[PDB]
């Protein structure tokens, strides 16, 4: 199987 | 999973069970197509779009091909799910109600299977209508700010997937966030206006058909004192007028004793004209003139009305 | 999972086993609505929104259907978390609690199914009441900068779920910044009220309601304590009362006596009145959590868009 | 995880590994009589932490114990020292959480660690939470360059810190900052004690010097009254820096840059007994300047004299 | 990660890999007599690193070793050279950190980098940390429009630089930083730096010893008066004098005609050109052709700043 | 990232997959005596990168090679040509940087690019880095509306440029090009030794430009170079070449070659290859394009290089 | 692959035999003189393709031949028409590149197509090569929520720019082009939309099979639609054909003899007032403001 995580990036 | 007309059977042995459970879960109160005030043009294009091929299927052979896609844009509260539910009632087509929470897809490469299986299942039941509410979600830019490397695949599968007939309806509150390849692919982009001073009289005189009105017949004056109400709020005005008929006799003090026939003395009471004056000083429109003009400018720069 | 009324049972099979634990974690008769003073309009809509459709349910039909939403708005110290607990005490309805923190998950596509499960259980149990706290988060217009993708689909699942059946739910919310709300969300909230700071007459009833139970002198002139506050937040009145009541310990020098000859000295102190010296010393020490411009901006906003 | 009083145990089954580890990571014998002055905050700590262990039948109804207190003042006056002193003198469990233990690259941890922190602080004991430099943690909500994933933390503090009439377990929230006017208008209401801390005046620095110099041999040339009269506007940290630089100036009277190794370890024993004369202070008084001129002190004084709860 | 003295180890499990790599990537034959001038900074480094290494029993109690120093000067003088000199002439491990080590794309990775750096420098040795160009990290804290991540870095420096609440565990750390603009540091970071020192542009005798230092190995004539060369360069920095020396060393090559000689007769004349000495005319021609990186306003502002708020 | 000399390879395990593409996207012939005038830049480049190639045994110790140079002056005066010439004349690798490549979306995704570029330039052969238009990259540090994404590039340049100095792997030479040299830092200009200002105009060199550009096989009677060189007043080094292109198009535009298709095409084309140019279309070109150059920029640059220029 | 001029053939046997089968399908009798405007682009195509290949030393050095051109304008101008016109006018192997010849199933075969194309372009003839919709394949290069595969295809495209052979491109949104592309694009000339004459032919051809009244005049219709692109005349005739239905009353009446009125509607014919009502309501797909941003771009960065 394969799962998915989530990220959080910031930008200007 | 049931069969269809003429006893055909879909050979859905090629997918997992929760996917077909999800897409069957996205599949009666008979409302009326004349139960909506205003907007004759969209009723015309729906009449040409789904009803007329049923009656006369020989006219739509060559250059008179019926339309295949459509989008309504306008402010919130003009009734964009109302036309959808009305045409879901008064038709023989099998309706559908897809959403963005209907495409959750905790695994990877499973929303794609859901959209492809949805569109292949839609070509099984022959007259079909697909209703995608609030296409702003899944309808951002393909190089926008917040995106993974997976939702772009959903948008591309949707663009190639749209090519046995179906017809897709959709709506938004914010039209300018839409794409370009998604915008050009939708054949008919229609602005929805707020109700004018003539439609409001029909709307408030039509909604008030159960309660006894006596002499508040200044419907021209009641449509003239409300300048810019947003359609879904005048029904709240009539509802607040009924509750203002209730609030006049102090019933917060009574606790159980004789509180059943006290309502019977108020279940026969009629809506007088004093209720509207206290009803106009307690309701303001939900918006300012900001989103309406922006939707008007977007429908003037791209709308094929 | 418990059973609802009439012995039915829910089929929660498509949902994962930690979502159900979360919503089960989201879920008596202590106080009453006569405790909270002032605020006549929200008391009226609460009386004609949950109490009265339990007595005569054959009257609220058709055009007279009961309300479906409300949102409080006002300064951050006037009391709008208290009324939610009060209506949690004085009803027979399954009261939920959901804040903005038990909706997030580090997997893709769990933050929209929690809301669906929440509304489905709120339909399934009873004529229930959900109370969404601090709705300014999960709010805001969707054409903002720096808006992440799941935080759009939460607002989408809310906006599709809050409409469209004689099973009643009455969603209510509270915020301090109502102008930073989404436009297509504050139409669904059928009643938007304003909550003012208390005037010169409610403050006396607050002072009298607070000082009950503690033995006081009969010479405390309440009218001067009423007319001298003049801009207090409504929650600062209770703090003024607590400072004036605990000030009697700062009168007797209890900094040196420890352990011995002290545990009886406090018993000598435990029946001492709270005289006017404590109030005159307490007014020089406590100032409001001020900046009355926020009250003025929320007043102008709810006087240009509010449905009283 | 540890156990608690009465041998119970928490059940952290709904949380992952690194969350309970990161809250596990935030969990001598000095007394409170080393602090110079500051009677009011000592009074509030006395009637808020010390007294509810001895006589608990008193603090019952309207006399419920406090729940929060913010110290505010110019930098370098003794804020973290009171916190460490109360940690070493009480019997409570002590949490020192600061604004770096609340962030992670995943989504949904910035709001969960706060909830697990408060639930463990309620589960263990009559505990004390000490958030240091909350001005970074709580800013204004409706502001310009605010990222979205900090509003969750602000709302989490704003809900959690006021939650029936049961559950007679106590949690005291202490916080320090030096820019208090950037706190949000709804989080300043939760902190019901907003004391201001002043710079030391001319009667306190004499006692501070007299506390700091005990333990090292000195002469009786020193006039502490003149030393208090010239050291005006200093911090506490500058006074300690002065009292240290005097002794290191006594090292500089013996030029040891030339010698290297040869009887050098036996050289300093002639220096390890030397006295600290008045010339040392007469050099260190012009060796050291104050840290910052008065512009933050006047802003904090004009702030706490209008919105401050002493 | 390598082990330390006494065979111990660090259990770096709670951080990800690339943070450990990005701090691990930030880790002889010089002398401390190669620094012309700067007596007091040599005094502080003498009495804060080299003396506790020999006699640690003297430095305890009120005579604790210092934990801070910031060098503020105009941008010409030697502020990097002194740090590399103390890095070579020690037995303690060195950590250089510039402003681009504390940077990542994700959210909340700068803080864990600073945390890991301080814990590693505490674990390995009585080490020394050199944060060069400090003004690009700590600005002010409430100015107009800084991002919501740099303020966390300032908070992390503030909460970590003082500490070690246990009165035991005297594992020494000494943080060193150089900048050009000291009137732009936050006050709560400024008092954490004791021993804030000013550094001047060099004097007459410093310039004389500089020209004496720079011209060794290369043969010069015996008609060179160093005194006029000192007295004419009124206003030169400590970095332009070496550039003047280099130009006076290459002017003897530009004096002959090698731009015209192309390929042929090039390798045959370069062997005898190395013995041609350096006369006064090369110094006069270089001195007419070299002007300082002037603008004496900045030296004035920095000296008035460190004369108002400075601690020597 | 292909390879380098002597068959080695790079190990870029520390960076992302989009950053290294932005630096890989930053990597015809020309003759040296094409560039006329400006003997000082030839002198500095000859004693900078030419002579250390054949003779590395002379340049050791105090005689270390230079590491910086700045060309100030008016726009369009031949800076890119000298860059290409010193690129192609030696066997050096040639990087080029503008302001439009040091820009990406995420915070801190620009500062890894500069360090990666300098690590590559030390990793490869002895190379030349041409950072053009640094008046936008390097402003002043203590400005008013200076972003918190602009100071860190300046700090990275200052820390990286002067790097721990004993017999390095290969020399690397950085150039510069700027139209406004008073708006530069006080800590960045010090890393730039050998600052030099170059002017635009000349009379005899403009004549030599015309003699090196006007390679028309016709026009044996258009020899009026004294008046053609007296009419180059205020014309920059690109202006005369654009004038020459204007004259060579007005050769076939002064004669009616418009709508000769079908009828009289090949004879009208082949009798035009020897067609005599005169001062007619040259006079058309003289009064067509006026120079858009102002003297204030030249005067202020000549004033700035007087005080702070190390020629 | 077939041969070229002077009897040679390409040997790409090191690469695959279906890549060459995927590019070989890219190499007519279009309107050579029948364009009644835009004589400047015909002049530059006559003097940059034919004349430096008839007299090869007339354009050299200072009279320089170009090497690239980025045509900007509407999606309704005849870029393909004049492109195939120069194809059938010159003696050049006219290649084509669409948005679909840059997709292949393997990895590493999405970059070799460009290389093999440039090799064939230099091998065959005095060629001229064209790439359509470069603003759709290549926008901004190095994004991160754009995955690295399109970044590498664009990198191999810029790596194969150094290809005699003349490269050519056409765009529709020109400020979306990258900064490194316009420095090689020596000219970006502004192309206005076609004329009164072009629409009437598609009007007369697109209305076959439909019963039309013989009172309609194509001149008055052809002169009042100034500003329309190619698909808008099809939209106009579609709205006319549906206005034919919209004249009657069919939503109100139902059931009783509806098919008689529908047979009368199928028997009915279009009026001139039908085209009037179709033209008085139908708007263009894009409003006349993207042309202003295009002219701002050609004024700012373009050579026009
Ligand atoms: N034109 C209308 N005539 C009668 N009632 C209306 C009309 N428009 C809105 N309403 C009332 O307002 C409600 C709003 O319905 P609906 O959701 O379709 O509006 P909407 O604009 O689609 O909302 P949104 O787009 O914000 O989701 C309806 O239930 C209906 O009772
Ligand atoms: N006017 C009031 N009437 C009754 N209780 C009050 C009043 N003002 C403050 N309180 C006290 O305030 C406490 C809770 O604060 P409150 O109810 O004001 O929440 P709130 O400040 O409205 O919430 P928020 O911070 O989100 O605005 C209760 O313990 C209650 O005793
Ligand atoms: N009033 C005081 N009594 C005793 N010691 C003091 C006093 N003021 C300062 N000090 C000494 O000064 C040093 C600095 O104190 P502390 O670390 O609390 O400063 P701070 O308040 O944390 O600074 P900031 O507010 O900038 O964080 C301490 O070591 C303390 O011993
Ligand atoms: N006091 C000194 N003794 C010996 N050499 C010096 C001295 N001051 C400067 N120099 C020489 O000047 C040159 C430049 O010094 P350095 O590179 O340290 O300046 P810097 O400190 O980096 O300036 P900044 O930090 O502002 O960039 C060095 O090569 C050094 O040899
Ligand atoms: N000395 C010269 N000899 C021959 N051609 C020259 C000379 N100077 C300028 N030119 C011509 O001028 C044109 C512009 O030169 P270059 O490309 O260096 O511009 P630039 O100086 O880089 O402009 P900017 O500095 O504003 O970027 C060159 O293409 C070249 O043809
Ligand atoms: Mg709707
Ligand atoms: Mg609250
Ligand atoms: Mg502190
Ligand atoms: Mg330096």
Image (cartoon, coloured by chain):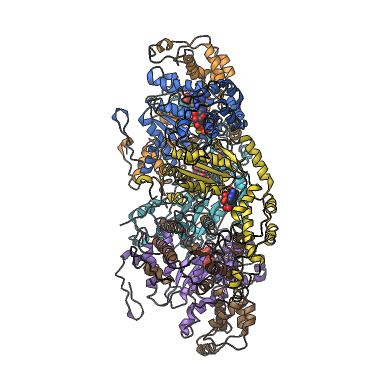
Chain colours: A green, B purple, C cyan, D orange, E blue, F yellow, G brown
Residue G18, compared with residue C30, is above or below; it is: below
The reply, left or right, for residue B104 in relation to residue D178 is left
Q: Which image quadrant is residue C239 in?
A: top right
Q: Position of residue B20 (x, y in %)?
A: 34, 67
Quadrant assignment for the N terminus of chain G: bottom left
The reply, left or right, for residue E240 in relation to residue G9 is right
Quadrant assignment for the C terminus of chain G: bottom right
Residue B284, compared with residue C261, is above or below; it is: below
Nearest to the observer: residue F37 or residue G268: F37
Nearest to the observer: residue F10 or residue E134: F10
Nearest to the observer: residue B223 or residue G226: G226
The reply, left or right, for residue G22 in relation to residue G199 is left
Q: Which image quadrant is residue C285 in?
A: top right
Q: Which image quadrant is residue C45 in?
A: bottom right
Q: Answer yes or no: is residue G56 visible.
A: yes
Q: Position of residue E74 (x, y in %)?
A: 56, 30
Nearest to the observer: residue D241 or residue C55: D241
Q: Position of residue E92 (x, y in %)?
A: 38, 27
Q: Answer yes or no: is residue D64 visible.
A: no
Q: Residue at x 64, y 77 (%)?
A: G224
Q: How many marks?
A: 0
Q: Residue at x 47, y 67 (%)?
A: G127
Q: Position of residue G50 (x, y in %)?
A: 54, 70
């Amino acid at each position: 199987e394969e799962e998915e995580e989530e990220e959080e990036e910031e930008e200007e | 999973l049931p069969q269809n007309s003429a006893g055909d059977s879909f050979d859905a042995s090629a997918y997992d069970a929760y996917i077909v459970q999800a897409v069957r879960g996205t599949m009666e109160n008979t409302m009326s197509l004349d139960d909506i005030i205003g907007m004759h043009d969209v009723k015309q294009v729906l009449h040409e779009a789904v009803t007329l091929p049923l009656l006369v299927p020989e006219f739509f052979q060559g250059l008179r091909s019926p339309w295949k896609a459509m989008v309504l844009a306008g402010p919130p509260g003009t009734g964009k799910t109302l036309i959808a539910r009305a045409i879901a009632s008064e038709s023989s087509s099998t309706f559908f109600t897809v959403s963005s929470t209907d495409l959750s897809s905790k695994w990877r490469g499973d929303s794609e299977k859901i959209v492809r299986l949805l569109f292949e299942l839609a070509r099984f039941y022959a007259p079909s209508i697909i209703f995608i509410d609030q296409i702003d979600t899944l309808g951002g830019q393909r190089g926008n700010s917040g995106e993974h490397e997976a939702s772009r695949r959903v948008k591309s599968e949707f663009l190639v997937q749209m090519d046995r007939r179906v017809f897709v309806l959709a709506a938004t509150n914010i039209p300018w966030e839409l794409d370009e390849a998604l915008r050009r692919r939708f054949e008919k982009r229609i602005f929805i206006p707020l109700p004018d001073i003539d439609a409001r009289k029909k709307l408030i005189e039509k909604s008030m058909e159960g309660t006894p009105k006596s002499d508040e017949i200044n419907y021209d004056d009641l449509a003239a004192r409300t300048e810019g109400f947003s359609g879904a709020d005048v029904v709240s005005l009539c509802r607040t007028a009924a509750i203002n008929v209730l609030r006049r006799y102090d019933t917060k003090s009574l606790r159980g004793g004789e509180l059943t026939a006290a309502m019977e003395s108020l279940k026969a009471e009629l809506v007088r004209n004093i209720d509207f004056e206290a009803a106009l000083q307690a309701v303001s429109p939900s918006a300012g003139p900001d989103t309406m003009l922006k939707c008007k400018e977007w429908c003037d720069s791209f709308g094929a009305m």
